[PDB]
Image (cartoon, rainbow, N blue to C red; front, side, top):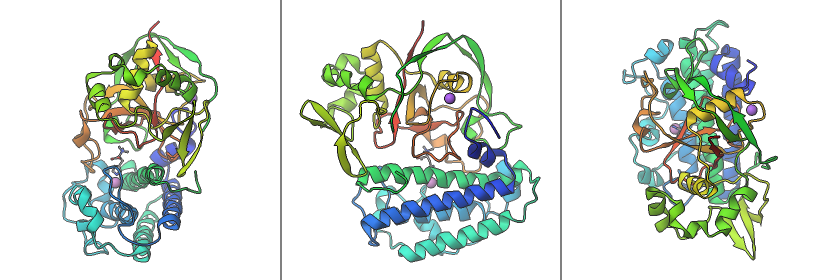
Length: 405
Ligand SMILES: C[N+](C)(C)[C@@H](Cc1cnc[nH]1)C(=O)O
Ligand code: NA
Ligand code: NI
């Protein structure tokens, strides 16, 4: 369980016995409910509760969706023990909630529709979470200590899914100005030498859970490189803004210039000018910017444009994964980091039972690697592939740079 690829929670969730997965499910639910109570403390109980935006979902919808997904792949799943060989579309038991599928299945309930749904109230939503988890843990307790990877697959999957939605709660709270009880400085900007080598990129078979987009592992050639030891700080990033870099379209790509054309505010989000200085928004509060913090809420175009101005580039996801795994002193986990790699399948990819996790998003999404401060330690992993459209700035995204010698 001790590795440089992730914290012990991450390896215990992916490969550990039922006791470890049980611990992960309880910890995930504790986090989910604490975030839910922090949203409730700001918003109260009205539904939908929040104004509309494409990158938000109504708080009670997120809670129900977390329960719905767990119940879909555990309690209602008639082929749990088959793991990745489960037939996605087999007929399942009915949910505790008759309208659950019509409300919480995201591939069926169009986004704008969610704001008008007659969802269960705040307390009935928590009852649904409670009962589904009680059922989940009871089925988990039937597994023996040496339970096979196939027997534990969906218990690991639903735990990781809830972790992803907790992080979404954290960055949606930033958008909404909601302060959280669970809620950033970097150390020295430095350069590290990555020598030429071979990397066996992706997840192997002996280890337990892998996301489908991590398969199959394959060899990749890594060229000699000098790579930042940490994400780009504000002190490093902001001279680009000060040199009028946002008013100089030569620094930007085709899609970057397009995106920059529509931009009302020509600097990173959640920043604002204050005299000759800067303020940054955090927990709905504006505070003087810390230059030694990581630059955050930048999109792929902003990261690439800084790189062109600086004469550097983004790493490929292979270069990133190699450095994270082989270079002590390469520090990650403060912000997700845009790479230069589009989200594409590895050689031998095959979609897993939750078929819509990766495959619909190839090509239109850019890979980010690492983790941010709001990523659960049970999820954060040097082989994990995050994927968002290159324009997104609501997520906790930044970057690091590199250049060949
Ligand atoms: C892996 N990311 C974070 C890109 C996913 C996580 C996810 C949550 N429920 C389904 N998938 C996303 O935002 O769609
Ligand atoms: Na490290
Ligand atoms: Ni989801």
